[PDB]
Amino acid sequence: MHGQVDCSPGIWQLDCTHLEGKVILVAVHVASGYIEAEVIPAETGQETAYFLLKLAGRWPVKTVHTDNGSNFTSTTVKAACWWAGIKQEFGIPYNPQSQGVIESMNKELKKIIGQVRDQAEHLKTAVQMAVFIHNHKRKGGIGGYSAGERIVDIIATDIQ
Amino acid sequence: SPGIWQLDCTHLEGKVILVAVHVASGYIEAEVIPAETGQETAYFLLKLAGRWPVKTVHTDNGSNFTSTTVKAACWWAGIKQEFGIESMNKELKKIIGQVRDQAEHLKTAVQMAVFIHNHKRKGGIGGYSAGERIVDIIATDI
Amino acid sequence: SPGIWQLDCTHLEGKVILVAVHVASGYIEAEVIPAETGQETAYFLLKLAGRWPVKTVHTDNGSNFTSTTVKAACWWAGIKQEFLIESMNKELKKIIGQVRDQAEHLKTAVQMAVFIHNHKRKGGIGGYSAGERIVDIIATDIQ
């Protein structure tokens, strides 16, 4: 939720969850807890490559971890990663508590989407609503910092 | 590498068999599992880790292998998982059929077959059975 | 002798644990079985005899060790049946308590404890582990 204190700023995890028969691709900045998410037409490697190219043109993505789905091991993905300078790593690191960072995120996210699902006509709107909420949520974790503020801050310090 | 192993699942008689092979010696361990689930595999690989020095394990993207139960056991045991023996599933099924008639149940025949494959004299001279080979490679490593 | 083994059944949480100890090294193999019968002892024996060169197996007169199902298994496997493990059992149960909470079923708790005993380096001026000694002895015997 608020990130892992011993993680580097370049690590990201990526997974696909499912809601109402739809495909939701998620990406989490392990160190802050910040996430990006989106509904996709199909669970293809072509769809996973677009998303990763969007994510690299904005954040300094060094390494991404994913499971071994056909969509994640495809050559379009692989090629995409090579182009972007991303080091791919198959297998989402295990954690005895959360099972997986990007795993507890897909859960928190379906939790939120569940609370605000009334205030939306399309799942696409709600997905984006949940992410906004997750990202602007502050907590004692650090002087009232949110996930969205932690990453720009972590990436700023790095650049500086 | 002595710590490298390959795991895979095969089918026979409307059943499922979990097969583990030591790539350096060709040594095998196998067992007929009630279902191709990640929990039956985790238990299996856990038995195999407190026995042999398992560092790395290679498998396909099969559900039971990309399961979290298996992921958790590998983390607890200190095993690095890789994805990406096929002959080993072939010889094993060959020997299973040579001793299948000596048993009613497949679970028993499979173990008779692993015993056979691991102890069968090779080269026309002792000391070279898959089972003899693994014990040497590990000791020469320790 | 590197081919001698001691087998015995111990109980925990109303379940049956079938323990096997390589007398020379101290290395063990444990397993919770459905029932304390010959069919289960046999099956277990054939897996152990398939990975390690077993010759003799020391058990008591338990109804499961003296069954013909177990006898025909030894015959097949070329194992002599003779009618340390006792202590081993006590050792094994001690570790099982240390990691018991780390597992849902006693099953894997038993396997976790076997992993811990075999990989633990201790005894004899502290150097090797029961798991490295067994491979060293059998390989020394083959060489």
Image (tube, coloured by chain):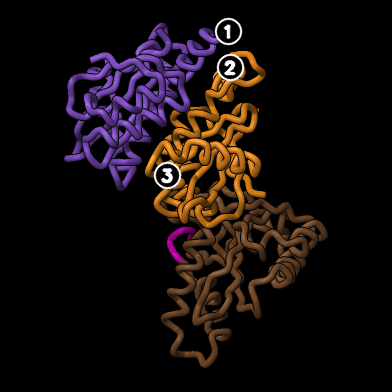
Chain colours: A brown, B orange, C purple
* Stretch in magenta: A139-143
Q: Is residue A86 left or right of residue B134?
A: right
Residue A149, position as x, y percentages in the image: 58, 66
Q: Residue furthest right?
A: A83
Relative to C61, say whether A44 is above or below: below
- Type of amino acid under label 3: Leu
Quarter of the rendering occupied by the C terminus of chain B? top right
Label number found at residue B136:
2
Q: Is residue C15 left or right of residue A113?
A: left
Residue C65 seen from this side: yes
Chain ID of residue with mark 1: C
Residue occupied by mark 1: C143
Circle 1: element type:
loop
Q: Residue furthest front?
A: B101
Chain ID of residue with mark 3: B
Q: Residue at x 29, y 22 (%)?
A: C7
Residue occupied by mark 3: B106
